[PDB]
Image (cartoon, grey):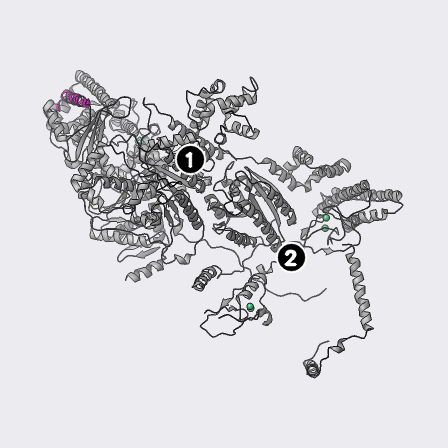
Amino acid sequence: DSLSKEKLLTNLKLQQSLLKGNKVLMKVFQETVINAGLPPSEFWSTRIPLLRAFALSTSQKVGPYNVLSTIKPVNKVNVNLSREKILNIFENYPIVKKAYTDNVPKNFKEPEFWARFFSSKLFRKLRGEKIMQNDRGDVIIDRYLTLDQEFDRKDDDMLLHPVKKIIDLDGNIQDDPVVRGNRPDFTMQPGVDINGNSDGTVDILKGMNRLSEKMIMALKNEYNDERNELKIDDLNESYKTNYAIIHLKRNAHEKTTLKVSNQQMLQQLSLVMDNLINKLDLNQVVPNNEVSNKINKRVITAIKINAKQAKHNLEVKSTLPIDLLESCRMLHTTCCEFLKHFYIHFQSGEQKQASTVKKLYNHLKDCIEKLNELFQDVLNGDGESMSNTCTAYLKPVLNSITLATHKYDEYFNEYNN
Amino acid sequence: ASLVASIVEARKKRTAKKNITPYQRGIIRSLILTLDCSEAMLEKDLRPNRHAMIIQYAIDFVHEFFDQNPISQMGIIIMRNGLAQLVSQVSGNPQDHIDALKSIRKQEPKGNPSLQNALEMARGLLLPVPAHCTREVLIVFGSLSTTDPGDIHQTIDSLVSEKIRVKVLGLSAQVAICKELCKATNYGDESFYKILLDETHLKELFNEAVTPLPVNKINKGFTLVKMGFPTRIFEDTPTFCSCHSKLVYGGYFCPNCHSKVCSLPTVCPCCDLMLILSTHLARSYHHLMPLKTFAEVPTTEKFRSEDCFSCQSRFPILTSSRYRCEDCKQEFCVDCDVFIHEILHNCPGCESKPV
Amino acid sequence: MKFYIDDLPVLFPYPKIYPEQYNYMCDIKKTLDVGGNSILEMPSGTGKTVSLLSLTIAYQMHYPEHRKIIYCSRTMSEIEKALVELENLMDYRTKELGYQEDFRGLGLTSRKNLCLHPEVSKERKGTVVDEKCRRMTNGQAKRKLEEDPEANVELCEYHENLYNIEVEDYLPKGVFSFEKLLKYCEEKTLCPYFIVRRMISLCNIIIYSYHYLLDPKIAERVSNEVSKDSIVIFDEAHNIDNVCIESLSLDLTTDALRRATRGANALDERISEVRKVDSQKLQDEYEKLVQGLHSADILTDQEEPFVETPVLPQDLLTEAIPGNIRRAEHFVSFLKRLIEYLKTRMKVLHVISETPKSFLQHLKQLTFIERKPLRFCSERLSLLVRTLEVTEVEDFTALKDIATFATLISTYEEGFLLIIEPYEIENAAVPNPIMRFTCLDASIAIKPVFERFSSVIITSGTISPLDMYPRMLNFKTVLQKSYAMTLAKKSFLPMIITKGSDQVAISSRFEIRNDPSIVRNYGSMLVEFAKITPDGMVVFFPSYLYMESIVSMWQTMGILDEVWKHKLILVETPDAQETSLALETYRKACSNGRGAILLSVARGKVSEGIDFDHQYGRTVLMIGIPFQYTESRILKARLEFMRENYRIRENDFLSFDAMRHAAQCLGRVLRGKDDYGVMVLADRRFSRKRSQLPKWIAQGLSDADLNLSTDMAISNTKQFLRTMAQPTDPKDQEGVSVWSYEDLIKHQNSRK
Ligand code: SF4
Ligand SMILES: [Zn+2]
Ligand SMILES: [Zn+2]
Ligand SMILES: [Zn+2]
Ligand SMILES: [Zn+2]
């Protein structure tokens, strides 16, 4: 289905779809392929989960439901039609879909059609309403009555299937074919009208049963056992988890990249217990104001250093021209994209990736030179008034990029040389 | 006579927690909470309504899950009007999903549920997930039925085949299909289809769902994983970030490809490798090193001490409230027992006692 | 698990067992020791069939008597249940002993269920199915094909293969299901009906319907190849009196009379043609009747009697045919004037009820036909059909019915009655007269059973009171006791809804049937229970017309549209086949958990062998008292006869039958102890009937539950669902409800 990497890369229409959904994706994609000419497959190669998420979001569909039961008759009536529910009616009733498609594009209008439909007795029959000759219906819609009837016959023919004997009431009533007793009660048998004909409640009940069967066979779509069926689980062994416990052997390496004696510590301990029982003065704790002054110097130096650390506690406010700010952000963004793709190629590790690595290396070099030329532009645009800040802002991505270039050169010298 | 009822209730409670095991429990988690926002949760039957409390409890659940287990990504898909709507991709930042849930606050829950569509797109979202990550889904449900487009059993079979588990927290009562899901997905266990009895029980259930789950021996995936500790810088100049492409005063620096990021514990956007701190990995060590329960000594027997070893307070006097750590042979009060067993994760008696 | 009774080794296919099952086995073995019959009542929520089957198998193997086993039920569903459980038990025993013992046991049913002749299989009337099978495998067809292979009267290759191989070669030992037998006969091209008809003398245990034991026509053959000293058990036959009643009751319609006239004329003209072309066969039949031979005398096994023996064989006439009906033309004129007499008595203007003796006296007053010819009619007709070779028997099935009626009414006089009423439908466009033959007693058909077999076990799950069945049927049992439900915790919650949401009472009375307020209440709690019901719910009205009215007018209110939004709704169709598709739909709907509702009559076809469990049995809407139709002269004559016989209060018996039908309705919820369900009583009048109700049922019926409304019914049901949604510690039931082998040992020592 539409789930492989190849399928997701193939769906150019879906790619354009979420493209048109976003705006920064036009920005990024335009710079990536329109401006830089990157292979758009490798563009989308990162965004594969996003593509699949968009596809699966677009791909779901609802389940069937009794749309005619949700239809209410609502003096006068005003049509308040919902197109999704109109198509729901179409899908649930292909007869109604057919009656739409041979009349509205031929004879009259859609709201006129639906007014005729709500007027029609075919609507009442398809809904849970007993048909009545007092009702006149709509003649145009009610011409489809026998067509819907033979649809019902064909659908019932499709719905017929053999039954399991374990639950077969037909086999149950065919237990004794020579039962000769008495005629059962009118009360518990299906009653009829005065002239022997039925009222049709059996028809409406078999119709709603047909609706149920249609729903369950819609469930039963494309998208022996009695031994298991008759198991009595209540007298069986309880399930126990096979979860594995874990122990932990403990032997850690010592931290890598004079010794005191009991006599000496005991001597000092005796002496300091003597001093402890001897004396203790709070007033002697006051310092000499000179080594204390050096303490003041050290403390104040620490305060100054950490205060300058705290002095640099939406992005930050900047005094850049807004266009050059956007341009440099754009260049940073596409350089980051190039760098990520180059790392994807490099950490892949194949000889098939070699020309890709070389070409992305060329693109990184081009981005470097374009960064330098941008630096020349902000040079002769500022006289290095804040072109220094421009260079420093674009610095770290450039450092990482050129570090990657050095890594590529080093591995080239490692393998080839 | 209330103390006898409290004692027998504590006995019937402790009968479940008598067995404490050092099972291997998942750390690289993958948790999905789908939400239904349908007509059922419009009931004000619990105050103020089911939608509001599940919103609040989901806020708490996000906070607790990210606090305890910051080494997982969190995705939320809402269910509404016969459609399941993705609102939260799996991410390391909880704040994104917090904002998405805040959007879910003001909107109106309505419609009917479709676990088939919900679990199908949850499966699809869970598809590009690495092997060590434990794919598991929490599902909240208030209906007693489910309108669906097609079969659920094919989805059940596919989910079992793709090694993803589920846990259902139903609202009203048991639904047999949800029981079937929990049993078949959960190796025949019935310890996953849970029904609350009040909002406090719902709170307790959410807290239970916070915890990591044990893994199975047959589901063996024992391997290594590449890891990298980054380094934080505090620069004078604001600098462009790799992730959000904007000027940052500080930021960690990539250990491998020397780029910079804005938040942790996150993977690299550039060298594409996970970056953490040792605090984050040690955070679950109480799960890795569980604590034994502490036993009250009986009031009839002679007592080692008459006041609490840890908090240093007098033991109250019918029964004896002296919870003993047999690993350190010291008895403690109930308050200290609660704190050491839940908040703390070490026994100071065992810290003082040399091994 | 396996333990020993005092001399009886016994194996249970599960490690666990219930103490109620243990006491049940104890009393059954006591009964088997003492000899005779006993009545035991047990809560059907515990396992029954497996335990009794294990006891019977152990009894046959351990004791040197090795008596056969007779078990009978109502439906193919119950028979298949017994087959599956028996297969599981014998498989477990084979595994436990490490080897398979020699064993034989099968069921018994119709060709409509069984005849795999694909051409014959495509008919819906089992009578037509059997008739075609006789037409092309009657032996006469085989002989005609043997003398003339060019004759186009084909034979059933299934039957031919069964001719080829022998009766022990038909099957290996053991038990085979209906499905397994279908696979086997599909493989080997064999007729399973014929197979079963030859397995009768060989099966260690035989299982068939209650009809095959009660009706003489389908029971004499069973009595032929059954051992007199086997073991007989009955299950859930607490409504078997109705089967007994219909075993000897018959009705007469105008069109049947017309078909009888046409068939008699066709037979008369055929006899005239045969007398014209070759009178040798007629003269041979006439002289064979002069010697006085009978159906067993002349007919072989491969040919079957046309008019099957309507009466019990203990009451048959075995002497010669009178000369007045001995000739074929004499017998035709005899039957025709019988038809004419019936047409004369047909055209009465009101309700007629006379004794058969009085009818006989009137008949011998008007015409000159005696009880001896009027009894010999069926045998003479069968012989005439056999000689006549008139196998196109379509016009003569009414002749079979009329000869059956004549023989039956000429056989008995006490506990039987004839009802003639001028309207077949009272409230129709025109009245249509009817003659109805009845059998006022029910214990007539059990007399061959009781006097042929001693080791007969009568037991059920919903039989109450025990003494009422020996009251209504002249039999006695050795011990009469029930079983209480030794429950650890409550699992079933019955409610008695004596009032609606507006504190308005409800009842199912047909006069107040079209009451809109009662409709509003009924639809009200129907909606409420639909909204709170998770998986599966069933509704049981007392009558189909009551349904059709009340469902059509809720369809007018559109309440069903609201019901659509939560579950499916399934209605008992008059077609059993569509009903089977409907119940399959309900089954699959509760399987996928989207939820569905069944609508079936209290006496309807669902209620007699279909169980519901753990999502299917969750909550039941029983609708009112399922009283029978009040103005039946047949019912009133029954009431008069049974009151005259056993001094039975009529209204009390009516309440008895109503509550027993209600119990049969409500007994299909709790399959295992793990299951749970809630019961409702949707009538005000039920509150006086808890004393009537079965003991284990009513023990959960609390005194606060005796008169409830919709609101606390809803609240209690929600709380019950909340309760049953919780797990349970095994320690609370490890020794009081679920018993290990050691638990049973400890209990046995405690008894010691
Ligand atoms: S011969 Fe066998 S298969 Fe054919 S109709 Fe008779 S019983 Fe059925
Ligand atoms: Zn950033
Ligand atoms: Zn990196
Ligand atoms: Zn303390
Ligand atoms: Zn300790």
Q: Is residue C456 above or below residue C388?
A: below
Residue at label 2?
B280
Taking depth in this image into account, of A393 and C17 the one nearest to the observer is: A393
Tag of residue C676:
none
Where residue C96 appears, as percent x and y from the top left, is 35, 53
Tell me if the residue at label 2 has its CB under 8 Å from ligand 3. no
Dot 2 surroundings within 10 Å: few (below 14), some, or many (20 or more)? some
Q: Residues within 10 Å of mark 1 (few under 14, many from 20)?
A: many
What kind of element bears circle 1? strand
Q: Which quadrant is home to the N terminus of chain C? A: bottom left
Residue interval drawn in magenta = C325-351
**Residue drawn at point x = 27 percent, y = 21 percent:** C430
Q: Identify the chain of the residue marked 2, using the numbered disc in the image.
A: B
Across and down, in percent, residue C544 comes to 33, 32
Tell me where residue C415 sits by quadrant: top left
Residue type at mark 1: give it: Ile
Toward the top, the furthest residue is: C276
User: Element type at marker 2?
Assistant: helix
Q: Which mark is residue C569?
A: 1
